[PDB]
Structure formats: structure tokens, C-alpha cells
Amino acid sequence: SMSVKKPKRDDSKDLALCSMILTEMETHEDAWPFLLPVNLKLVPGYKKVIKKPMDFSTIREKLSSGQYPNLETFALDVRLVFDNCETFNEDDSDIGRAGHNMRKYFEKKWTDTFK
């Protein structure tokens, strides 16, 4: 509350560390469904159904331009990529499996870097 604060966690490295995580997600072999925005002209249903599209290149641009206020808003966009994927793709599909795999890979790096 006013004039009452928990001890200050060092957040000076968070930007660099989120960039590293994102590099690792970008270079994963199952990243291909997520590298670029879904083409809303060429994929019927996507625009109407997925209210907030998100992809790794859009996260990279937001990160590089100071549009993440903190590490949690960064994790929310990464998770949005996978939540979108599950909303639109059957579990038993190449893309549906890719999304589960990448969400696992992410959540481990996240815990190991920050928790």
C-alpha cells in the first residue's frame, strides 16, 4: 500500500531474457505454424472466429519497440498464440500437435528462467 513495498525484484534483465526465449521459440522445428500472422484473406473463418490473432513475428516487433510493459504481458501474448491454435485446429493434426509441443517448450523455459 502507500509507502509499504515488498523488496524490489531485479527486472533489469527481463527484456533481454524474454528476447532469448522468443529466439528459442523462433528456431524450434515446430514453430512454422506460428512464425507469421495467419493470412486473413486466405484462411476462411479465421478473421471472424479468432478475435485476437497473435504470432511470433508480431511478438518480436512488440518486444523490440517497448510495447510490453512487463514480463507478464509478454507471456500473455505467447500463450495467446497457443490458445488461438487450439481454438482453430483439431488436436489430431500437424498444427494442433505443433501448438501443444510449443506451449510445453515455452512453459518450461518460462519457469526455468523466472520461477
Image (cartoon, grey):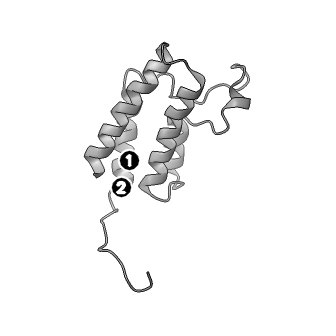
* 3 is higher (above) or lower (below) than 26: below
Q: Evaluate if marks 1 and 2 touch, with contact meaning CB atoms under 8 Å apart.
A: yes
Q: Quadrant of residue 1?
A: bottom left
The foreground one among 37 and 77 is 77
Query: Callout 2, which amino acid?
Result: Asp
Distance, label 1 to label 2, CA atoms, is: 6 Å
Task: Please name the residue shown 54% across and 54% down the image.
Answer: 67
Tally of numbered tags: 2
Seen in the picture, residue 100 relative to 64 is either above or below; the reply is above
What secondary structure is found at the residue carrying circle 2? helix
Residue underneath mark 2: 14
On screen, residue 92 versus residue 105, left or right, reads right
- Residue at position x 47%, y 22% from top? 32
How far from the left and from the top, in percent, is residue 43?
68, 20
Residue 28 image-quadrant placement: top left
- Please give left or right for residue 113 compared with residue 32 in the image: left
Residue reaching furthest to the bottom: 3
Q: Horizontal and vertical percent for residue 24?
A: 35, 34
Q: Is residue 5 left or right of residue 115?
A: right
- Residue 43 numbered tag: none
- What's the residue type where badge 1 is placed? Cys
What's the residue at 36%, 31% (across, down)? Answer: 104
Label 2 Cα neighbours within 10 Å, binned few <14 / some 14-19 / many ≥20: some
Which mark identifies residue 18? Answer: 1
